[PDB]
Length: 251
Length: 251
Figure 1: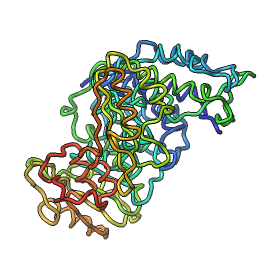
Figure 2: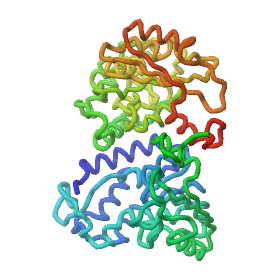
Figure 3: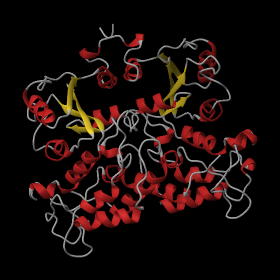
């Protein structure tokens, strides 16, 4: 893949914009300034082969960038990027990882280390399908684990219930591996929202298959649990983009 | 009123974020680099009493920041900020002034010049109502005229048709003063979308009152004209935020 251009300028630019003008009424500011955060981010991967990472590498960065999260508004998502963020509505309804300082800054960005100066590769990054798994998932995996550690009250999980190739819940998904396992006793309930795409075959359903496995795990950690499919607020969003779909006929 | 802190850092940060990562396949990049745009903007208002600005103050800045806009996708809005922007969908369905470079950079910010050094106040600014209208509307008024002048094809105008104190169309609104008068012969049609807020009394309707005055003005200028009240896609969007409104009952 293609590395993001001017990585430090974008990082610092997003960091300053965020610091001064974004989510002011939803998330707190972090104590560290933008250049301090950059330094921690950079050392997690710099001057090392691009696959020479593990869950421990960005530990200092995430430690400095962690914000206290709004209670009952944390949302995790799997396979449904646009729908979950459209629904969260830039933090007005829910906060997504991409709404937090570390997520907002690195969202959609691409980068990787190299041993030779300047320590990062500005031309090409591994297809990562080449780095082992613990290296491929070092950044978003520690991001997910730190975010999950700070969640409070009700957490929401939006999943794709229409993918015949990917169960709604998987033990090796980001939520499976680093999210659920790191939720603390500060979490009270996991609320699953299963997306049944408009015009497609339903694959997964609450109370069965992978979603039942998830329910078992969730209750084994003493958390409450509930699950719904295409709730009204979500269906209307889907219909706005495809008003002639059958699931959208009005009375 | 309290001005935005570190205005230059914010302006420059947002400009860099936009440059490298935003609207990449929807709007063209601007030729001037972020540092030059900042110089033009700062010169428009610095070292002048805020009340002495007029429609010509930011003319050069908008000349530098103006982007060619995609055909048939320009939208104007009046009294309906959130709805028009949700529908517009970050440039994917329509373009709004706030998606353009100058709009994105200054959106929501507060600033003011002063005659004393350093030529702008970073602590406090005078409420603008005190100043003459040409001065209060100096920046966004020139912004609109420049945006409007760049419009091609069909332009869309989303208005509040549920306000008994503010006609959907007014000769003194930004659209009335800076938009419609600045639409060139490159515009072929003005398509009005009348927003009827869920649960509110309907006030304006296509073909009557101010929308009839507007229609007459539009036709007198040789543009086609059409008008719709709560088109389905818009209603669904309204329903997502109030799934139980009477207007949203599903078959």
